[PDB]
Amino acid sequence: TCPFYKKIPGTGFTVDAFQYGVVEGCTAYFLTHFHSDHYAGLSKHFTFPVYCSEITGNLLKNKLHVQEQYIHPLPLDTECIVNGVKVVLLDANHCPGAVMILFYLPNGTVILHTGDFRADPSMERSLLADQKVHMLYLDTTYCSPEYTFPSQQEVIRFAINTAFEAVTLNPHALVVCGTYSIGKEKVFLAIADVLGSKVGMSQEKYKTLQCLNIPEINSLITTDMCSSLVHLLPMMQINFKGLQSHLKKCGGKYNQILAFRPTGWTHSNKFTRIADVIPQTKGNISIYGIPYSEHSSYLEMKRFVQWLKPQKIIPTVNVGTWKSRSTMEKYFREWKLEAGY
Ligand code: NI
């Protein structure tokens, strides 16, 4: 049974609700992005209309095999009518293809569903500038003040400098980057660009990247592992055992691995600056955990919400405990009293 925070009142619409079977009254199923917790349930046998971005629709067709007749891609930043209701898709600053959805209800209420997002001041000059929002369905993944992390640009500066230094000292070092979903592609693309290399990967990962409309992608990636000195591997293999095993396979081409694990937040964020990050090392293998987030920090979230001034907030993450729900409600009330809405 579909929970309330996935239903859009006054419509036949749901958001990210494919794991509940046929939802009573649903005439259109929106999908915000191609992450498994949100697409859970979609397959080639699905026969209801799915509304999404172009990039998400490429992934549904090629990776999940959803038939073409049920995929409805919409352009961004464009007023569209769906089943008699005006909607707009906005860039969510999350992974490739990720959107927020603005719903203009027949009764005059305006609803914003963020999907998953990383709030940015540039969102204050989108189509959100133009009118009032009554209800906000909010990605509250990091809604607590302990959740701090640097800008994505600082994190990429750290990774590029770390990789370029290591490989210039040792031309026989290999760089490896972990992945388990779409998102965070700038980590491996920026490192391969500074090293003058394509990124090597499995056929399955190549296929996924080929769905993402990245400019000049054919110049940037390859399935020929041997020609490349930046390899992608599944996140589970990013440990001393998995990496040892990988170095064996390269036929004595390399004598050192430097590996990156992009995580979300970890408690080593509470004491250490990005500049001061050190790896875990065993012999000729070193592993860096780097805090590259595609979700809002607490401060970015608070700024967005204080600017938007919604009348009501419905959290979409951390909703399963009374303690989480109570904590989040307290911060919403602080924010509202501080800003005066
Ligand atoms: Ni996500």
Image: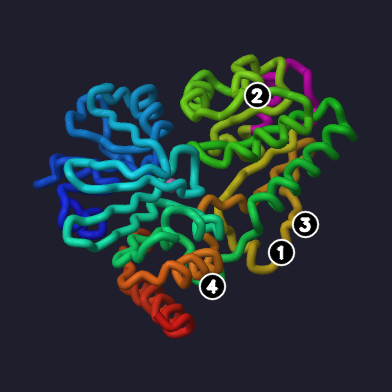
3D distance between C-alphas at marks 4 and 2: 38 Å
State which region is magenta.
243-256
Question: Which residue does the numbered mark 2 point to in the structure image?
Answer: 220
Q: Nearer the viewer, mark 3 or mark 1?
A: 3
Q: First in sequence: mark 4 or mark 1? A: 4
Question: Which residue does the numbered mark 1 point to in the structure image?
Answer: 272
Q: In the displayed orientation, state which residue is furthest to the front.
A: 130
Above or below, 322 against 247 in this view is below
Q: Is residue 238 visible?
A: yes
3D distance between C-alphas at marks 2 and 3: 28 Å
Question: Which residue does the numbered mark 3 point to in the structure image?
Answer: 275
3D distance between C-alphas at marks 3 and 1: 8 Å
Q: Residue at x 34, y 24 (%)?
A: 61
Q: Is residue 314 visible?
A: no
Q: Position of residue 103 (x, y in %)?
A: 28, 53
Q: First in sequence: mark 4 or mark 2? A: 4
Question: Which residue does the numbered mark 4 point to in the structure image?
Answer: 145
**Residues marked 1 and 2 touching at CB (< 8 Å):** no
Q: Position of residue 255 (x, y in %)?
A: 80, 27
Q: First in sequence: mark 1 or mark 2? A: 2
Q: Nearer the viewer, mark 2 or mark 3?
A: 2
3D distance between C-alphas at marks 1 and 2: 33 Å
Residue 217, by quadrant, is top right
Q: Residues within 10 Å of mark 1 (few under 14, many from 20)?
A: few
Q: Is residue 85 left or right of residue 173?
A: left
- Three-letter code, disc 4: Pro
User: Any atom of ligand 1 within 8 Å of the CB at mark 3?
Assistant: no
Say if the magenta span includes residue 244.
yes
